[PDB]
Image (tube, rainbow, N blue to C red):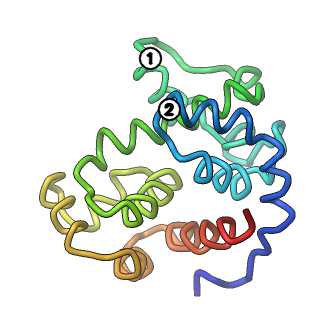
Amino acid sequence: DYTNPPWNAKVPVQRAMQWMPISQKAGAAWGVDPQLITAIIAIESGGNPNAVSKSNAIGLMQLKASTSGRDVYRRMGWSGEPTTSELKNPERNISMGAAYLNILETGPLAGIEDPKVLQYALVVSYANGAGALLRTFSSDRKKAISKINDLDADEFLEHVARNHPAPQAPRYIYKLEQALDAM
């Protein structure tokens, strides 16, 4: 049961909303929905810009220097990876998070047609990687996308809950809907 325990979104979303001006700016620059950015902030850090997880995920959107941080650096045309200090900067963190969502949308998840299925695919990919998601459909990226396109949002969630190896995957979707209802 990925909905258990329940997650009350009120506090973490209202805290995350204090970052909205940055989220709207970053979202407009990268073509990313600021409500999704706000949801991710609420879910990942509860709006605490200094959060540091066990696995060294840092800041408002819990970006990890060696994984998503480096992916965004490559998208900017840079080598290396951000520092912890850089990831604690709220503006830098949220803009990098927005950039990462754009990278997912325009790279591995390109061709998803339904914008609600795409929303769910984004959070699941954000949480455990686009590869882990797509491989539950096919080792071939295009066949994977074609299979995703055969599903609606509620069927996508069912698939993820049954077939995704990470329990966090379907729970992210549940939390997303909890977060959205609180905005």
Q: Position of residue 64 (x, y in %)?
A: 60, 36
Distance, label 2 to label 1, CA atoms, is 9 Å
Residue sitting nearer the eye, 170 or 13: 13
Q: Is residue 36 above or below residue 75?
A: below
The N terminus lies in quadrant: bottom right
Q: Amino acid at mark 1?
A: Met
The C terminus lies in quadrant: bottom right
Q: Is residue 179 above or below residue 122?
A: below
Residue hosting label 2: 99
* Callout 1 secondary element: helix
Displayed quadrant of residue 21: top right
Crowding at dot 2, Cα within 10 Å, few <14 / some 14-19 / many 20+, comes out as many
Q: Position of residue 49 (x, y in %)?
A: 81, 38
State which tag comes first along the sequence, 2 or 1.
Answer: 1
Q: Position of residue 127 (x, y in %)?
A: 53, 55
The reply, left or right, for residue 144 in relation to residue 136 is: left
* Callout 2 secondary element: helix
Q: Is residue 103 above or below residue 42?
A: above
Q: Do the residues under discs 2 and 1 have CB atoms within 8 angstroms?
A: yes
Crowding at dot 1, Cα within 10 Å, few <14 / some 14-19 / many 20+, comes out as few
The reply, left or right, for residue 98 in relation to residue 59 is: left
Q: Residue at x 18, y 57 (%)?
A: 139
Residue sitting nearer the eye, 101 or 26: 26
Q: Is residue 19 above or below residue 9?
A: above
Q: Amino acid at mark 2?
A: Ala
Residue hosting label 1: 76
